[PDB]
Amino acid sequence: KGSVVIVGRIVLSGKPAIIPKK
Amino acid sequence: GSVVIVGRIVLSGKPA
Amino acid sequence: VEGEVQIVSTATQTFLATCINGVCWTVYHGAGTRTIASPKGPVIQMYTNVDQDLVGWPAPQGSRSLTPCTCGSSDLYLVTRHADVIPVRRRGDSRGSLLSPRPISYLKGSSGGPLLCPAGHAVGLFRAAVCTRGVAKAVDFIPVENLETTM
Amino acid sequence: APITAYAQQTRGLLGCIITSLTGRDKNQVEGEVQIVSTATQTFLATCINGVCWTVYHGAGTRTIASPKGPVIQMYTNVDQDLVGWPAPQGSRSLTPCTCGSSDLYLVTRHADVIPVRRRGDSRGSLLSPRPISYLKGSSGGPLLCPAGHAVGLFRAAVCTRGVAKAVDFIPVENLETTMRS
Ligand SMILES: *[C@@](=O)([C]([C][C][C])[N]C(=O)[C]([C][C]([C])[C])[N]C(=O)[C]([N]C(=O)O[C][C]([C])[C])[C]1[C][C][C][C][C]1)C(=O)[N][C]C(=O)[N][C](C([N])=O)C1=[C][C]=[C][C]=[C]1
Ligand SMILES: [Zn+2]
Ligand SMILES: [Zn+2]
């Protein structure tokens, strides 16, 4: 069969952050 | 006078 | 990226606003009856509640709403205007004790911010710091219920 | 600090299909949980102690596409309904729950953390019921204790009239038993 593919991720280690302006 | 948004905070820290 | 907490300011001060249930809530003692700015002109508050020290405008752009708490936890976390997280033990309906008291300056400018539960869901809105001799040891807050009610 | 999560899609349908066949994935990895797919379904995989675990009912006995080509499962336990591959270089691992917490938090593929009240070593009730559709695609996802440690992996939903009120999970202990066997 075909391989299992990572199509995205979920990050739990992120901390509240001020969104940088761009 | 209005309240103005001067910045934002993303709680999960999503950089995206 | 969309933020749940808006760092806002009037001519007088600077504080925070938190989007919960599609409404951008903040403290009446910061906003008053002020209208919120938008690229299409000022937008009037959808809710004004002087008694609860609560006001609300429709959620702005570049924002995302927070989910109200449903696990009834007492281990709260306050997020400051500098993105600092402060553990707070819920001492009551609308009161909580910092697990580590901080100088009042540390909490200054965070009214309107959220008090998150262990799941990052909204428990309440930081109303005012309760301090002794310039050191904040506790905080006052607007339980999400009030918001859910005001809506 | 509170448990907060965010999701990022790393590849589309067509890129996924080519990668599935070639078995060679050159994309950079980040995160504790990986959104995973096969030609038939999409679910989650959680890295715990250097191993990328997921549900056997999802991964079957498939290899995982990595930069070096396909990677054979390290652990496979049809009974435990678990499969594990070496955690991808780049991922961050969760650690098993030490304190036996009663209040758990399920992280969905949408990066929402929903609280569940533990009602057994393998079950917990959603404090706030959600449609069964909301939970689709989250099998293999972690159930975290307040400290953010892995208590289990989402396996099945106790659905009724299309609404899920409880969830069945593979407690983090079955992992050790699976590695031991
Ligand atoms: C998971 O594997 C899912 C989570 C959906 C709830 N789990 C299951 O499908 C399991 C598999 C069996 C082998 C345990 N079944 C169930 O959870 C079923 N309940 C059940 O067996 O209950 C028993 C209890 C008493 C222990 C439910 C019953 C109601 C209907 C749904 C099954 C998972 O997420 N799989 C990936 C997936 O569903 N992908 C979908 C897809 N087509 O790729 C999908 C992804 C994203 C959005 C929609 C659909
Ligand atoms: Zn909660
Ligand atoms: Zn724990």
Image: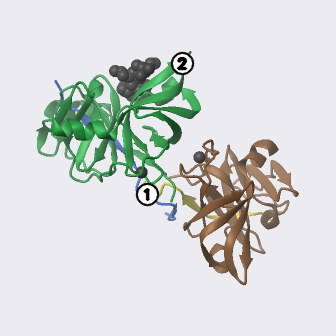
Chain colours: A blue, B yellow, C brown, D green
Write down the residue under mark 2.
D162
State the quadrant of the C terminus of chain D: top left
Residue C37, position as x, y percentages in the image: 73, 59
Q: Residue most toward the bottom? A: C133
Viewer-side residue, D4 vs B6: D4
Q: Chain of mark 2?
A: D
Q: Quadrant of residue C39?
A: bottom right
Query: Residue at the spot x=47%, y=58% of the render?
Result: B13
| Element marked by disc 2 | loop
Query: Answer yes or no: do the residues labelled 2 and 1 have beta carbons within 8 Å?
Result: no
Q: Is mark 2 within 8 Å of ligand 1?
A: yes
Q: Is mark 1 within 8 Å of ligand 2?
A: no
Viewer-side residue, D2 vs B7: D2
Question: In this orientation, does residue C60 appear?
Answer: no
Q: Quadrant of ligand 1?
A: top left
Cα distance in 3D space between marks 2 and 1 = 33 Å
Query: Residue at the spot x=13%, y=39% of the render?
Result: D71
Circle 2 Cα neighbour tier, 10 Å, few/some/many (<14 / 14–19 / ≥20): few
Q: Quadrant of residue D19?
A: top left
Q: Residue most toward the right? A: C51
Q: Which kind of residue does numbered mark 1 sit on?
A: Gly
Query: Residue at the spot x=37%, y=31% of the render?
Result: D139
Q: Quadrant of residue A9?
A: top left
Whether residue D134 is situated above or below residue C56 in the rendered picture: above
Q: Chain of mark 1?
A: A
Write down the residue under mark 1.
A14
Residue D79, position as x, y percentages in the image: 24, 24
Query: Residue at the spot x=17%, y=36% of the render?
Result: D75
| Element marked by disc 1 | loop
For residue B7, side relative to residue D103 (left or right): right
Residue D121, position as x, y percentages in the image: 41, 35
